[PDB]
Length: 352
Length: 14
Ligand SMILES: CN(C)c1ccc(C(=O)O)cn1
Image (tube, rainbow over all chains, first blue to last red; front, side, top):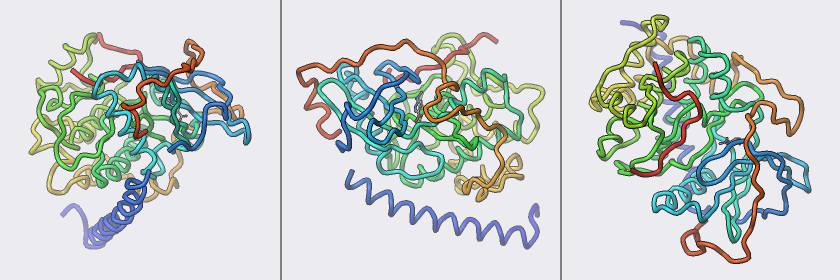
């Protein structure tokens, strides 16, 4: 076969160790998931700079006044979180983040709320978004893309074992830490799903066909999105690429992907099996689960345990000028945070 | 090869 006797036995033992790890991880997750609040307040922090913006608020670099430690504070305007799924998703995000623990997931430190806003205070990751670095350099070489992809594979193996779907993979949500490893942020679309779920949500370029077609769907949408991410990292642009969302959706559902001439055949083979419309054939969704991905030829040089233990030398280390340095983030319009004298949407956010 | 090159917003519904 492809493996000799010694290589096959080592792989088998490796997969039994994964099972052992995930069983312990599920025990630790459930303890925090069953008993999640109000671990700080706004005036405990100095607000420094906006690091990113969305339709519901912003993420700001903040400095804890007492300790001087820096954090990233996500501020959500409760009155902007108006639509039904916008509300449920915000509760998903907080509850999941307080319960998970993995080396490539951003760590939540505090959460609280006031009359106007919801707040989630996270570890500050000063290396910036993968997105910026990718757009600046153009594309990543296949070994460089593979290093990041392996971290996402392990992170999804972890999340999916807890019945969590992530649902918003893209370079904008992948921060680079001081050692060059990934930290996944923005769990606004993450959800605990034991089988199928039905919300039409995500980012157009990264949506699996079954989402676009209003089909009930499962964790395999994350493996489709991994295919999009790997393609974009290695090409510099995603596989379904058009100016308007409706045009993007048409390309996704077609079942057609073209590859740059510089893609290795191993990479193209992996991507055709991730970007697979037929769910009975999509890698990650078959009887051998995530091992069809981890054992694919394109990952043959990947030491999965060494990636997890962060023993592998990273292809890129961001420059850091010191604590609180924001040089690796883009600039955004600043808007003062106003807290109303009246409580807004108190009942819609009781559990936060 | 015309497509979106800036940051892409996620959509919660529709
Ligand atoms: C741009 N956004 C989503 C950010 C930026 C930075 C961080 C962080 O340092 O933890 C989190 N989210």
